[PDB]
Image (cartoon, rainbow, N blue to C red):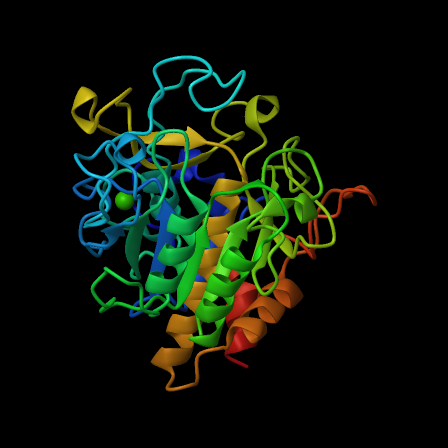
């Protein structure tokens, strides 16, 4: 499928480039992810972005701190509106932190997952007939481990005190987020719960040019940890690495690869603070945060295709094994000491093997 989105051909090398892309055109001839729910645990969403409407569920906001959420109270609330994660001043988040504008990170990641495609508007997305369940866990200066753990439980169909039962349990969780520290009990138990309910958990390896074993949730057991490659098919300068990394997706190499080829392109906003300070746009961002949703959406294409053929969905372990075994070996040598998994996720090869 060669969709008609105006910016797809020029910008979206991560979808269609022969060395650095995920082989999406051919995969789309087989599945678009219809009938699957991918939970995006992230900064929230711009629910009325014109290139996302139609593919979103209401979701929920698990941030339990008014200063972080920019809401009126410390309560968790329905919906996942991103209020903006900007920070006005240096050193507000930690020593040497630098002031920055709102990211709309969650809207970009949700775009990779399920941006409306072949609709004559903006960009394409990978599992563009799936639905995104936006679960807001990150705001000003990031988020809280206990919030993120409860979001994992709820997203995957588990019960959380004080939140109404999730009517839309997710077959796939994407966590484009990370922090220092090896995986603890709280994270691990929530992840184990999600796995026990059949949910595949896909996480970003992290951007510290360091061993993924030292960060969470990258280092958790049972998850798919995703490194980042460039348009060239080689490791990015920032990607974490190590034996915990299962495979990679296109994260964008940054300035070395120029514009557009250094960045992943999706729905976003140019707003610097609140949503109202700017307007809907398409933004280029680089990171393992951009690689992870490519792999999460391929998981959604596979589950969709199985369901469509009256076959059983894969269990989480089988899903990880499949994504690894079908990854495209890297077209540039990866150094021995910085392994980033078996290859770049290959949407078509994953579908072909699942449907054999
Ligand atoms: Ca579009």
x, y percent for residue 257: 58, 26
Q: Residue at x 40, y 19 (%)?
A: 100
- Quarter of image, ligand 1: top left
Nearest the camera: 315 or 123?
A: 315
Q: Locate the N terminus and report the quarter of the image it occupies.
A: bottom left
Q: Residue 96's x, y, as percent?
A: 54, 16
Question: Horizontally, is 125 left or right of 281 in the view?
Answer: right
Judging depth in this view, the residue of 147 and 112 nearest the camera is: 147
Q: What residue occupies the far right of the structure in this picture?
A: 336
Placement of 72 over or under 297, stated as above or below: above
Left or right placement of residue 317 versus residue 91 in this view: right
Q: Nearer the viewer, residue 69 or 8?
A: 69
Q: How many marks?
A: 0
Rendering coords of residue 27 (x, y %): 46, 62
The C terminus: image quadrant: bottom right
Residue shown at 42% from the left, 75% from the top? 197
Residue 160 higher or lower than 275, as above or below? below
Q: Quadrant of residue 84?
A: top left
The quarter of the picture where residue 231 lies is: top right
Horizontal placement of 310 versus 187: left or right?
left
Where residue 154 appears, x then y in whole percent? 33, 63
Residue at 53% x, 44% y is 17
Res 346 seen here: no
Would you say residue 187 is visible in this rendering? yes
């Amino acid at each position: 499928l060669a969709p008609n989105d105006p910016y797809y051909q020029a910008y979206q090398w991560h979808l269609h480039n022969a060395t650095g892309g995920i082989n999406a055109p051919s995969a789309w001839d087989v599945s678009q992810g219809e009938g699957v729910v991918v939970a995006v645990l992230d900064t929230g969403i711009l629910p009325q972005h014109p290139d996302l409407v139609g593919n979103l569920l209401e979701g929920y906001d698990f941030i339990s701190d008014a200063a972080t959420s920019r809401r009126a109270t410390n309560d968790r609330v329905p919906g996942a509106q991103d209020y903006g994660d900007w920070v006005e001043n240096d050193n507000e988040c930690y020593t040497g932190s630098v002031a920055e504008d709102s990211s709309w990170h969650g809207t970009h990641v949700a775009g990779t997952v399920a941006e409306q495609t072949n609709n004559g508007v903006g960009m394409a997305g990978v599992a563009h007939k799936a639905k995104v369940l936006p679960v807001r866990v990150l705001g000003k200066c990031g988020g809280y481990l206990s919030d993120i753990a409860d979001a994992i439980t709820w997203a995957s169909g588990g019960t959380v005190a004080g939140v109404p039962a999730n009517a839309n349990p997710a077959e796939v969780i994407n966590m484009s987020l990370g922090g220092s520290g090896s995986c603890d009990g709280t994270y691990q138990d929530a992840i184990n719960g999600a796995i026990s309910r059949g949910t595949t958990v896909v996480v970003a390896a992290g951007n510290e040019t360091d061993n993924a074993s030292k960060y969470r949730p990258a280092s958790c057991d049972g998850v798919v940890t995703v490194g980042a490659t460039r348009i060239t098919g080689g490791i990015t300068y920032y990607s974490n690495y190590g034996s915990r990394v299962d495979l990679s997706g296109p994260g964008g190499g940054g300035s070395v690869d120029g514009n557009p080829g250094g960045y992943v392109w999706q729905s976003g906003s140019d707003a610097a603070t609140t949503p109202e300070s700017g307007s809907y746009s398409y933004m280029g961002m680089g990171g393992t945060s951009m690689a992870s949703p490519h792999v999460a959406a391929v998981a959604a294409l596979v589950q969709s295709a199985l369901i469509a053929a009256g076959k059983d969905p894969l269990a989480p372990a089988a899903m990880r094994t499949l994504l690894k075994e079908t990854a495209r070996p890297f077209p540039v040598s990866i150094p021995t000491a910085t392994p980033i998994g078996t290859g770049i996720v290959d949407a078509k090869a994953a579908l072909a093997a699942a449907l054999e």
